Image (tube, rainbow, N blue to C red):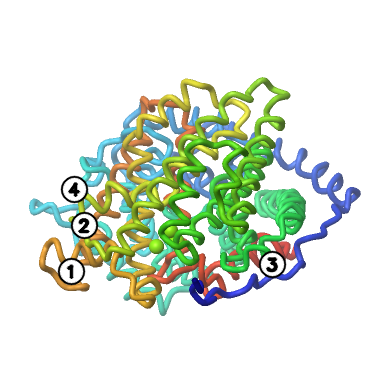
Amino acid sequence: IVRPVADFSPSLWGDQFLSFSIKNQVAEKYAKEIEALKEQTRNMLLATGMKLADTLNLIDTIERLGISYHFEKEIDDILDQIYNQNSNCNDLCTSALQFRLLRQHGFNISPEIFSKFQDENGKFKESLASDVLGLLNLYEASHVRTHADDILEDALAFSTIHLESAAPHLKSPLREQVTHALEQCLHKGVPRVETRFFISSIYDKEQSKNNVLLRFAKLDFNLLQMLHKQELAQVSRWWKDLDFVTTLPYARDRVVECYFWALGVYFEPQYSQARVMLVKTISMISIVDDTFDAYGTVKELEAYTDAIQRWDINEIDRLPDYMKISYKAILDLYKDYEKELSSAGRSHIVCHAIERMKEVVRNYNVESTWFIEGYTPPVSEYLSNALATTTYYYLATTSYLGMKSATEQDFEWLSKNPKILEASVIICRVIDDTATYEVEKSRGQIATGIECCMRDYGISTKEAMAKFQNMAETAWKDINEGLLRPTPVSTEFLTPILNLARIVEVTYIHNLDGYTHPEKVLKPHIINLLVDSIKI
Ligand SMILES: [Mg+2]
Ligand SMILES: [Mg+2]
Ligand SMILES: [Mg+2]
């Protein structure tokens, strides 16, 4: 009979993104200067006879400035040289940076590089507590551990306590860099978010800074931002022409946040078509989610689920009027993808994303059934269903659609649920369940994962959320390990999965629902990435 009642916030943004006209003259000006600065930077990278520590800081600086996607060949060659030369005689600062940069790029450098900084007990020499730059680089490095790196077991706690201790008396911008590192490490942050912070709050205020790199980074950031705003304008126009804001009023209106997620998966210009496909899907499955999660009677969701499995416009008449709206929108979206990909003969690959979406919808229907029955499964059984309901198997598959170079063999690998994809999915699940345990346990929801975890192990909500946190930490060890050479597929198809995990950490930072309540977390990120340019 009657439905639930509306609890969701409206879009924060109105139509402020709907229209954006690129100032073409400015665009060409920026692009023209960048080409000159690009070659100056390349020559910095090819300069012969640099010290190890200077070469690492140059690579680090360029990566954090968001301009390393211009120099993948150069940076790879350099790190390849460093990996295969074994220079072990350096201080903590250089050693920890060396370790991090090589691991992030898939070079399996031994964690024994850290032996010289530990005593016979394997715990870090406390005499290092006053090397702030060394601690900072150790702190960052401690976040790329795999399961083989238990020698670094103490690195995070050791560096954290002493960085906290030093911070209030540090000079700027080092103090700000440390304070922000402690809030958000580099490895698990969204790359555009960290780049924007680094460029304007840190590097712009360093006395040592290289002016060519700073100017390069500002111009390149503001130039990509113009492309992002164009993309968001086109997606805003598509979303508005759908008009789910009035015809499907029960669902979250978050296409801007969805674009932010797509931007986190990749920011580079060559992934423009990919981002636009990805965001359309994210916002569309967000609708489907809210239909099971907050409007769908058990019967109604059954008709919807079967309709999705058969995947055929003939099925719309078995559905309620309001479900006809979302269902045809879904079917039309995939005919769109097919035509958009028809050009490059990449049309066939769409059925991979479709099959993964059928799978999501099947488990929405299960977990709905669990809530109406009030079933609290064992945690193993709960995860066996709740992993796919993250949508991360599905967004990961989708993310490949627009990538011009994704082949069938790539989708084939992704379909076998590889360990890197599984870890990213696990991180999303357990963090979502912690961040939104109350948000959901408001509406009498007893199907929550935490509740399963409490019932299963006979432990409190304390130990529950803890035990979930650990699964996230184990999963990060598996992501880091999935990045190491020889990689199963090209790094290009691993980075989107890594970035999915990063987006989880960033959106649900400090254990809050950042997607449903964007005001706290996501609004600042969106303003910094898509509203305000960097003051040049
Ligand atoms: Mg939901
Ligand atoms: Mg849901
Ligand atoms: Mg949830």
Q: Alpha-carbon distance for marks 1 and 4?
A: 26 Å
Label 4 or label 3, whichever comes before in sequence order: 4
Q: Which mark is residue 388?
A: none
Q: Residue at x 36, y 28 (%)?
A: 485
**Ligand 3 near label 1 (Cβ, under 8 Å)?**
no
Can residue 83 be seen here? The reply is yes
Of 215 and 253, nearer the camera is 253
Label 1 or label 4, whichever comes before in sequence order: 4
Judged left or right of residue 419, residue 514 is right
Q: Alpha-carbon distance for marks 2 and 1?
A: 18 Å
Q: Residues within 10 Å of mark 3 (few under 14, many from 20)?
A: few
- Check disc 3 and give the amino acid type: Thr
Q: Nearer the viewer, mark 2 or mark 1?
A: 2
Secondary structure found at label 3 = helix
* Quadrant of residue 278 within the rendered picture: top right
Residue tagged 3: 246
Figure check: 458 above or below 24: below
Residue tagged 2: 377
Judged left or right of residue 331, residue 167 is left
Of 199 and 283, nearer the camera is 283
Residue tagged 1: 463
Of 26 and 370, nearer the camera is 370
